[PDB]
Image (tube, rainbow over the protein chains, first blue to last red):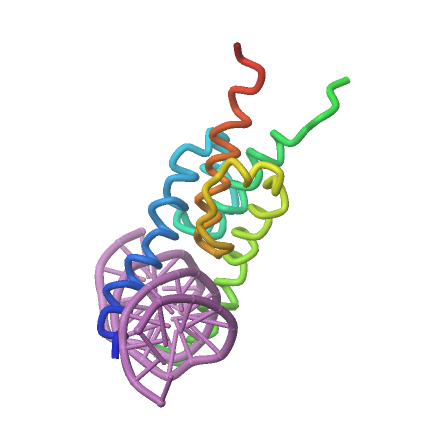
Length: 63
Length: 63
DNA sequence: CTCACACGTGGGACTAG
DNA sequence: CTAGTCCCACGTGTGAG
């Protein structure tokens, strides 16, 4: 039963979710992801602010 | 000594990272995605994407 | 303690024999 | 049926502070 690999595999898989996610804040220019309620530089929070630098960025109507 | 049952501490906390991936999905452009090689619609595979957009949105107009 | 975390695990679409 | 892929998510033993 390939769960034997599914391990070696679904690890590589769950890993991808990291390399990249890592590589988001890795260069979230918006360094405020450095300064706030941030209870963890690893997933969630970083991603909360990760959507943020974009959230600033999606400003499309300069007066 | 909830060193087993503390359980919920994971997902009840994980939930954020879920939607973090999700708001990361709200301000990302489907219309963009055509550029990106389809990976599969996953809670990992698209963290890949938010980078793409972001890495991009930065140098907007530069020529 | 409270956090955050990476492992296995059963797994349920989907596909190729 | 049989198993090989996908990627989802829970339940945890652990380090860290």
